[PDB]
Amino acid sequence: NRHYYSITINYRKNELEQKMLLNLHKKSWMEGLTLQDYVVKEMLELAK
Amino acid sequence: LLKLFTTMELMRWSTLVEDYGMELRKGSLESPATDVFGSTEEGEKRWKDLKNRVVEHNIRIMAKYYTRITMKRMAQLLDLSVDESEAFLSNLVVNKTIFAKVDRLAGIINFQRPKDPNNLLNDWSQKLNSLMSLVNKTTHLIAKEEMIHNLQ
């Protein structure tokens, strides 16, 4: 702190980019194409 | 010889008697056909091994195939009758590595050998294949539809 201090850094919005990053993220992770898996028969024994 | 081995499809024993008993009289080489077929004390044991070949020629493809056929129909498509079926199929159920299925109950058999321990691969095959083909249906049918409207 001898002649130093940190500064404010916000992670600001990009309206050109934020909703489409959200589009990428969500709509590529919710089943990818959203039509794929809608494992199952051995997790029976695993869960019991 | 090779045609008796590629997919094998059935065989008639008497057509084999024709094709490989006219070779025991027709001569170009004559000594190997003697040693295998023309001989008696060992060549006739090799005729018995040829009978093993024709019946295993039956049994290999009939272990590949024939789910829900009957039995007299089975023996007449074996080209060997029902008592010959019990002989010729007992001496290859002693092979004890092919699982088959017969019943009597009047003289009628059935099939589907493992008694279907499956509700799993139904889901696997059916749903994973069909659903992933359907998610391909978008990615390439709308691709070709956009292609045919690029060229329109």
Image (cartoon, rainbow, N blue to C red):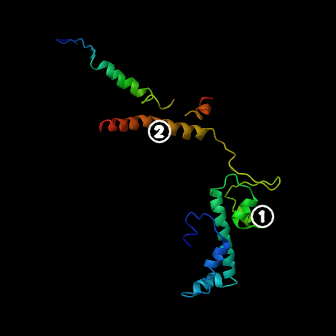
Residue extending furthest front? B152
| Residue B125 place in picture, x, y as percent | 55, 41
For label 2, the SS is: helix
Quarter assignment of residue A27 = top left
Residue extending furthest left? A3
Q: Nearer the viewer, residue B149 or A44?
A: B149
In space, the residues marked 2 and 1 are separated at their CA atoms by: 47 Å
Q: Which mark is residue B82?
A: 1
In this rendering, position of residue B136 left or right of residue B59: left
Query: Is the residue marked by circle 1 packed among few (<14), some (14-19), or many (20+) residues within 10 Å?
Result: some
| Residue B152 place in picture, x, y as percent | 30, 36
Q: Which amino acid, mark 1?
A: Val
Q: Looking at the picture, does residue B27 appear above or below residue B14? A: below
| Residue B79 place in picture, x, y as percent | 70, 67
Q: Looking at the picture, does residue A30 appear above or below residue B124? A: above
In this rendering, position of residue B58 left or right of residue A12: right
* Residue in view at x 60 percent, y 63 percent: B9
| Residue B149 place in picture, x, y as percent | 32, 35
Q: Nearer the viewer, residue B15 or A41?
A: B15
Quarter assignment of residue B100 = bottom right
For label 1, the SS is: helix
Is the N terminus of chain A in the top left, top right, bottom left or bottom right quadrant? top left
Q: Which mark is residue B133?
A: 2
Mark 2 — on which chain does it sit? B
Q: Which amino acid, mark 2?
A: Ser
